[PDB]
Length: 291
Ligand SMILES: O=C(N[C@@H](C(=O)O)c1ccccc1)c1cccc2c1-c1ccccc1C2=O
Image (cartoon, rainbow, N blue to C red; front, side):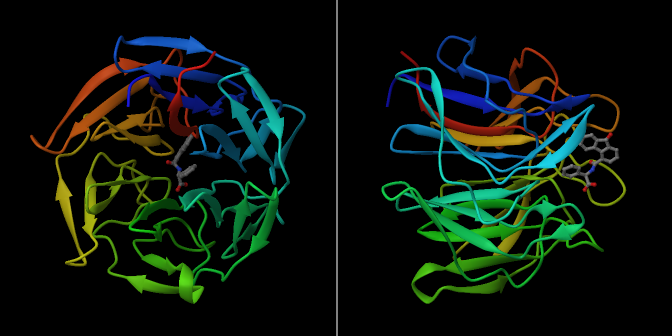
């Protein structure tokens, strides 16, 4: 269990960013690692087999905006990125979850197109294949996996921001609606901790949110927990050693550098570090330290 870092890839501040930086909770240090080959915001990060994957996003740049169909792999042992097979379609503001060593890419946008489509990547074969689409088109969607079931939470369908959520049952290749959240959330951070799916922050159509709610997969209810110190949309999120970490985002005024940590035992958030610069739209995942 030792030696793991929180990696943050990409993001946005004025333009999309290529940064890969890794935080060590055991000593408070940050490392700057190999830049992404292409800057991207609105991507997602995940880890399979000790390798960090960066999925989708968009390169917002002075010379144009290009939505990304890319899958790229970072190996901490070599500090190098390698391209993988690309997805069927570009997906900005994507959500991603991993089940049994397979990466699911969910929703996202391509220009004015808001996807309901979903595809699954097989690292051993370096292939993507489409699976059943969601019941709702969702961009800015939060995704997490609990008990080998995949959840898609909130987002924007092209007309309205959403409080709805749905679950994918892989052995039936089928999506079903679950109880909706109490709050509309686009661009929330969504993760799994213990028996619950958490949705932290986001934008409700009027304001960035500091509230946080969790869905108990047995009781099918959403319950609010302690709010974050900062309102934030387009935040990064991950879980490490039993605590939720939220990174960056936009608070309605500033691109945040703060990283907050949620302790479920005390139901409290604390500010634990700051990124090297404020940014939104990052991808985040946990794997072994490099070299
Ligand atoms: O929170 C906002 N927007 C969310 C939405 O539209 O649902 C969203 C959700 C997910 C990804 C991107 C955006 C929002 C509202 C007004 C002004 C601004 C933003 C914003 C967000 C991120 C970076 C910069 C800004 C910014 O200047």
